[PDB]
Length: 55
Length: 55
Image 1 (cartoon, chains in turn purple, yellow):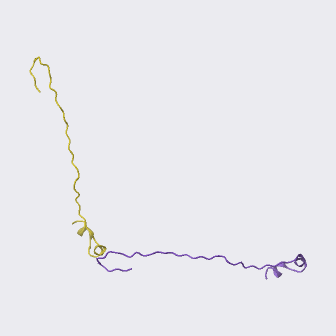
Image 2 (cartoon, chains in turn cyan, orange; image 1 turned 30 degrees about the vertical axis):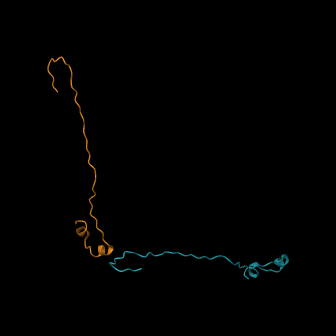
Image 3 (tube, rainbow over the protein chains, first blue to last red; image 1 turned 30 degrees about the horizontal axis):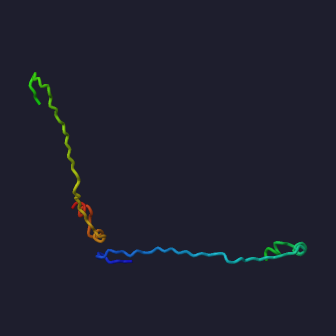
């Protein structure tokens, strides 16, 4: 605030320092799941890091 | 005290040593006070130890 100069009143208005805070939280689970029977894991997937992992 | 020589009354008058005392006490508070609002301390008073301290 501002006050006059040489005013007979001698009061000052105090100010406020209110500090806020918010937050973020985990609320989702993004997943990709693949199930392979042993037959097609053995003799249907030529290479793993090209038919499974990359997709 | 004084007594005659060869006086058969062999008596001596004792003497007393009463030591006195008297004290002083602080009873007055001599003071000189000055009040300066910040406006007249910043502007009106040019030099301090010529308007405040010396008087």
